[PDB]
Image (cartoon, coloured by chain):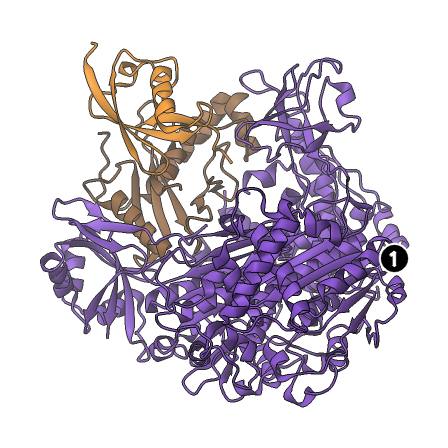
């Protein structure tokens, strides 16, 4: 319930960025935070955690993302 | 070569039991070819329809890695809107194996129905959902024959 | 109006059909046949002009043999033009080469279209001739080379229109939004590629109805993903769709006479690092002619200071006459003019080959008008090629002539430096177009002619009659012989000094021939020069040069574009450290339908036969295939079910596949996703990169539908060994029509594996039955290979509303043919030899070397400093990521190898591989560890690969991953196991 926590995010080129966030932050809020730090347009990349595509409407606590977790960045359109 | 050297560093990072992702069981073909990987795809998500499955696949890296995208093929082929009848799946283009494999399990639960390859599975995903779930559940159970002996898989 | 597309195949893809037809109606006159003259004449004759005429009544001197490859010691005394015309006509039987005897009356220039004046024409005569050409509409082009310097002049008359500026394909792309202010927004993650000043037409714009009529709009680039065309409020409002195509508008450019340009020149810079030296050399080359007038046609003496100081005065006197050249407040740069006077008598092959190809391309633009011509002037120098005076000093004694053919080369570098060039041991990989130009320049340099040097050239290919256009060392008499062997004897006739010094081999460079090119071969060489055409071989030679720490001179051309790369050990990076799928399903360009048709051509006539040939010859194939299975079993079932008997059955199979691939599968796709289908978000399914297809109704009178059946039937008949009375050169429509009009075509209706494995007949049923798989050949025009891919691709193009392509355009995309013109090949080869001068001095200053990039279409010349090899570190120990490696002596054991790395290097070896074979891994189970930890490196490879290391192998390259003293992975060099 609103506990501070830092999480890691892996990019496509196996590079890890460290972010300081809270469980009361939406994925869209976090996705916009990775946008300004890496340079990727918002439409090109999404976020996957333990094989779960994070929707922009939910928050970090909605996906049971505790402290020192690792997010993953994947293209939005990648199907054959 | 800069291709075999790059493949080694990514093969050790995905098979070291300290950094290994529990969602994929990676082993080399004949334990000697670095450019041919036998990967076992597992969906650990409990709410997913593909839960409990072990879908065997094969990755073949070309000689011009990473300047050419590698091929990914399900053996055997699975029912998915983004998988050809040949079992193969298009890999797009600086990219790592970890990003590609994670991109694959993400497509398994959220298929890109707008750009379909199996038109049968695509029309079944949206128009006949009950039939698509039945084809996947039957596909997951037939996958249990492709388990080795002694392997345990947690949720973690 | 016919063009030999068998001889000019690679050249037609550069110049086009229309431009080559104008070239075949233009008579070219070249004045002066020194090294620069014969280099221009060779490339122009090879390019195929209507007629070639040369004029040079001067007697052949031994010093002229410095750059002219068509002169021998036996020709000394006779006229340069007469002895060269014979050897020039041999290059192209379609181009007659004549000799103009006396140019006393200038009215003889009226029968020519392009006049070329080389260095043998005085500046006073160049102006007299240009005044007659400019006032008569004749194109005038001049050029001269002074040592390591040179320039060129272009005057194409007072009226010249550039219809095509670049010769490239017009850039096109899809539009996602057109704002009312004109901001044309592209689709997601697509770059328009346009630049300011471009012009574009529009298509498929739903709402701006008057925007699609073909009116052109000026492009104002806002960013890499958008451009602006002005307010489009008059045309309506944007809804969806849109495809823009760049259109090249004509540009009528006006030229000034040579007299006008000497006073107010317009420069085109060959190197922006030396863009100030342009106006300096403009007065220097003029002063060289004033010096010749004041000295009875004499040039400034070699390394002479009295003449060099007089030239500086003439340049200063000219600066007062022409104050616009240098401009106000800029000094004369006496040091530059002094170097120009020192080399005024030099004849450098690298500079001649450079300007020879450059001016020749300007002659081609003069006859065809295909590219953008040179804007009135360009100057170029390669002063960085001069060796260090501390090792090879230059003065009036070292650079004096020695009564040899290299006198004009010694005049620049000195006698001691030319001896080292002759004592160099070089390796030329490939004897193609670049290799032929490479051996010619090395023959003029005398490279390898010394008692300590040699030349090794290897090429496993033979000479063909079609290659005689792009390979000028070969003649019709040599077709069928080996490329490297004939090119060896070709240069020995130009310079007999190389006789017995060229080792011509016919062996392919690769891992297959590591016994022939062993350690003793590579280590004895000084440097290696690449003359290859494919990337697979280039990377191997590059990885070999990195292993043995030898310099590599890399080059390559693509049409009018070309580049050079210098690779220095321990200093710069190598050539390896530099530089769809969905599109087949939803095509929007002709490239995607060809890739779809090319893959269909493989599964029809190549993969189906290999599966049947293996199902019949391997008994366990059914059980072996279980390790794609349904597609393979279906391929063998369809290949043995509809087995054709005569050629009439093959026509039926091709017509049925036409209905399946282009009518039924399209209706089945349109059944699941109609033209009005919508996605989850409510967006139209068929939008943007996706085009709603339409089913094809077969029409035998449609050229693409007809040839899909002819080629499809002829190729299937080749698989099943069926022959026909039809002519393989001309199919008859009425015969194919009576066969199809009597067929019953099934209508369309919308739609485990152990059953399939039981439907296959036994191999014993078909005893001796063999299918002949089709081996794809792009260069044969009678095997129906290109006929199928062209017809099949255009049919799918008709489905998705893509514009069809002809055979020549499809052969280009399918075969991945690299265009090659003779002008860029000679120019690029010259730049390689100018860097070769820097390899002889063993220069280590990275700024002295220069990587070149040329685009003769603009024309653009740019040079960049080579990139230094990236450095890394482990345990605070810096190393070179490209060149550094670990040297281990003896066939060490795996256990002692890890011990040597934890003690001497502090690295815990976690993995170890040998080529493409993984040998050791720290995460192996204790069973795999103890088994391999006690084996040496040679026995470790035998255990893993089941193959023995041959006795001719003396070294082994091992890739390793290791952790530092903190337990984290760190990049480390590779290992060389010295057996
Ligand atoms: N691996 C190789 N070994 C020997 N020669 C080669 C190799 N690859 C290409 N070549 C030669 O390189 C030449 C290609 O140059 P070009 O004719 O200009 O395309 C031909 O003579 C080929 O036979």
Task: Please tell me whether residue C630 is drawn above or below residue C747 in the rendered image.
Answer: below
Q: Which chain is brown?
A: B
Q: Quadrant of residue C602?
A: bottom right
| C708 displayed left or right of C314 | right
Which quadrant of the rendered structure holds the N terminus of chain B? bottom left
Q: Quadrant of residue C239?
A: top right
Residue C769 pos. (x, y %): 62, 68
From the image, state the color of chain C.
Answer: purple
Would you say the beta carbon of the disc 1 residue lies within 8 angstroms of ligand 1? no
Q: In the image, what residue occupies the spot 37% across and 75% down?
A: C522
Task: Please tell me whether residue C12 is drawn above or below residue C545 in the rendered image.
Answer: above
In the image, farthest residue toward the top: A1
User: Mark 1 falls within which chain?
Assistant: C
Which quadrant of the rendered structure holds the C terminus of chain B? top left
Residue C154 pos. (x, y %): 72, 54
Q: Nearer the viewer, residue C75 or C132?
A: C132
Q: Which chain is orange?
A: A
Residue tagged 1: C732
Q: Are there few (<14), some (14-19), or many (20+) residues within 10 Å of tag 1?
A: few
Task: Please tell me whether residue C927 is drawn above or below residue A76 in the rendered image.
Answer: below
């Amino acid at each position: 319930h609103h506990h501070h926590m830092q999480i890691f995010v892996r990019t496509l080129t196996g590079r890890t960025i460290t972010l300081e966030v809270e469980s009361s932050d939406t994925i869209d809020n976090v996705r916009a935070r990775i946008q300004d730090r890496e340079g990727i347009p918002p439409d090109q990349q999404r976020l996957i955690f333990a094989g779960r595509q994070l929707e922009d409407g939910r928050t970090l606590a909605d996906y049971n993302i505790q402290r020192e977790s690792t997010l993953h960045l994947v293209l939005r359109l990648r199907g054959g | 070569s800069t291709a075999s050297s790059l493949l080694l560093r990514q093969y050790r990072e995905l098979t070291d039991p300290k950094k290994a992702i529990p969602s994929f069981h990676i082993e080399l073909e004949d334990d000697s070819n670095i450019f041919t990987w036998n990967i076992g795809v597992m969906v650990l998500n409990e709410d997913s329809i593909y839960h409990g499955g072990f879908f065997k696949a094969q990755m073949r890296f070309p000689e011009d890695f990473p300047f050419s995208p590698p091929q990914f093929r399900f053996t055997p082929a699975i029912y998915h809107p983004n998988v050809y009848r040949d079992g193969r799946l298009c890999i797009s283009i600086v990219q790592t194996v970890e990003s590609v494999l994670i991109s694959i399990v993400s497509l398994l639960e959220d298929p890109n129905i707008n750009s379909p390859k199996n038109v049968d599975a695509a029309v079944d995903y949206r128009k006949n959902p009950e039939q698509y779930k039945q084809r996947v559940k039957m596909e997951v159970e037939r996958s249990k024959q492709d388990i080795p002996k002694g392997f345990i898989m947690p949720t973690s | 109006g016919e063009i030999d597309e068998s001889l000019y195949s690679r050249q037609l893809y550069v110049l086009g059909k229309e431009a080559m037809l104008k070239m075949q109606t233009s008579n070219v006159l070249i004045l002066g046949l020194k090294g620069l003259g014969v280099e221009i004449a060779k490339n122009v004759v090879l390019a195929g002009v209507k007629s070639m005429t040369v004029f040079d009544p001067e007697p052949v001197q031994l010093a002229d043999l410095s750059t002219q490859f068509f002169l021998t010691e036996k020709d000394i005394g006779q006229k340069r033009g007469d002895v060269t015309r014979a050897k020039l006509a041999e290059l192209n039987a379609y181009v007659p080469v004549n000799v103009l005897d006396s140019l006393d009356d200038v009215t003889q220039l009226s029968q020519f279209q392009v006049v070329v004046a080389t260095d043998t024409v005085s500046l006073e005569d160049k102006v007299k001739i240009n005044e007659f050409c400019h006032s008569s509409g004749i194109r005038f082009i001049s050029s001269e080379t002074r040592g390591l310097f040179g320039n060129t002049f272009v005057d194409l008359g007072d009226e010249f229109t550039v219809l095509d500026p670049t010769g490239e394909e017009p850039r096109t792309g899809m539009v996602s939004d057109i704002e009312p202010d004109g901001t044309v927004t592209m689709l997601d993650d697509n770059r328009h590629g346009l630049e300011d000043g471009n012009f574009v037409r529009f298509s498929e714009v739903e709402g701006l109805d008057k925007l699609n009529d073909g009116t052109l709009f000026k492009v104002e680039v806002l960013g890499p993903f958008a451009f602006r065309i002005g307010s489009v409020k008059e045309y309506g409002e944007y809804k969806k769709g849109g495809i823009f195509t760049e259109v090249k508008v004509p540009r009528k450019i006006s030229f000034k006479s040579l007299k006008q340009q000497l006073s107010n020149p317009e420069f085109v810079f060959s190197d922006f690092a030396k863009f100030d030296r342009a106006a300096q050399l403009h007065l220097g080359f003029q002063a060289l002619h004033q010096f010749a007038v004041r000295h009875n046609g004499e040039l400034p003496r070699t390394m002479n200071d009295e003449d060099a100081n007089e030239l500086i005065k003439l340049v200063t006197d000219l600066s007062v006459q022409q104050p616009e050249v240098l401009g106000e407040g800029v000094d004369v740069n006496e040091d530059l003019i002094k170097e120009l006077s020192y080399q005024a008598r030099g004849d450098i092959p690298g500079v001649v080959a450079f300007f020879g190809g450059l001016v020749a391309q300007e002659v081609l633009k003069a006859c065809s008008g295909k590219f953008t011509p040179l804007k009135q002037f360009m100057y170029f120098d390669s002063l960085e090629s001069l060796p260090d005076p501390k090792n090879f000093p230059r003065n009036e004694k070292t650079t004096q002539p020695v009564n040899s053919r290299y006198d004009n080369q010694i005049a620049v570098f000195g006698l001691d430096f030319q001896k080292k060039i002759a004592n160099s041991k070089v390796f030329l990989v490939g004897s193609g177009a670049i290799g032929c130009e490479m051996l010619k320049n090395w023959a003029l340099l005398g490279l390898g002619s010394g008692s300590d040097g040699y030349i090794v050239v290897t090429d496993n290919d033979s000479i063909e009659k079609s290659n005689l256009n792009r390979q000028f060392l070969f003649r019709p008499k040599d077709v069928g012989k080996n490329k490297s062997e004939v090119a060896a004897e070709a240069v020995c006739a130009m310079n007999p000094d190389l006789k017995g010094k060229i080792n011509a081999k016919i062996d392919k460079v690769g891992p297959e021939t590591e016994e022939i090119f062993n350690d003793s071969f590579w280590e004895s060489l000084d440097f290696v020069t690449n003359a290859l055409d494919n990337v697979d071989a280039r990377t191997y030679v590059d990885r070999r040069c990195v292993f043995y720490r030898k310099p590599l001179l890399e080059s390559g051309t693509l049409g009018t574009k070309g580049n050079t790369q210098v690779i220095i050990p321990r200093l710069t990076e190598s050539y390896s450290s530099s530089r769809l799928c969905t599109l087949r399903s939803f095509p929007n360009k002709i490239d995607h339908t060809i890739a779809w048709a090319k893959s269909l051509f493989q599964g029809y006539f190549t993969d189906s036969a290999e599966n049947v040939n293996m199902y019949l010859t391997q008994p366990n194939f059914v059980e072996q295939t279980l390790k794609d299975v349904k597609g393979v079993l279906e391929s063998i079932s369809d290949s043995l079910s509809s087995k054709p008997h005569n050629f009439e059955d093959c026509i039926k199979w091709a017509r049925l596949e036409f209905e399946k691939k282009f009518n039924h599968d399209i209706k089945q796709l349109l059944f699941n996703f109609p033209k009005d289908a919508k996605t989850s978000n409510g967006e139209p399914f068929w939008s943007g990169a996706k085009r709603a297809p339409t089913p094809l109704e077969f029409d035998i009178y449609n050229n693409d539908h007809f040839h899909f059946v002819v080629a499809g039937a002829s190729l299937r008949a080749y698989n099943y060994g069926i022959k026909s009375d039809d002519s393989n050169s001309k199919p008859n429509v009425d015969e194919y029509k009576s066969v199809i009009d009597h067929m019953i075509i099934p209508e369309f209706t919308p739609n485990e594996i152990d059953q399939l494995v039981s439907s296959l007949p036994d191999p014993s049923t078909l005893a001796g039955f063999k299918l002949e798989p089709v081996d794809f050949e792009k260069d044969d025009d009678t095997n129906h290979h290109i006929e199928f891919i062209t017809a099949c691709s255009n049919c799918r193009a008709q489905n998705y509303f893509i514009e069809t392509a002809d055979r020549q355009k499809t052969k280009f995309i399918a075969g991945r043919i690299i265009p090659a013109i003779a002008t860029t090949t000679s120019l690029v080869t010259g730049l390689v030899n100018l860097e070769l001068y820097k390899l002889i001095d063993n220069k280590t200053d990275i700024e002295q070397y220069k990587n070149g990039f040329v685009n003769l279409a603009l024309p653009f010349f740019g040079f960049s400093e080579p990139i230094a090899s990236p450095k890394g570190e482990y345990n605070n120990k810096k190393y070179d990521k490209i060149w550094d490696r670990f040297d281990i002596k003896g066939d060490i054991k795996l256990s002692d190898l890890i011990e040597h790395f934890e003690k001497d290097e502090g690295l815990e070896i976690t993995m170890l591989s040998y080529g493409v074979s993984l040998l050791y891994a720290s995460f192996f189970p204790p069973k795999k560890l103890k088994e391999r930890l006690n084996l040496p490196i040679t026995q470790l490879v035998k255990l893993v690969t089941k193959k023995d290391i041959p006795a001719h192998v003396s070294t082994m390259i091992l890739e390793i991953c290791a952790d530092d003293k903190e337990g984290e992975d760190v990049e480390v060099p590779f290992i060389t196991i010295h057996l």
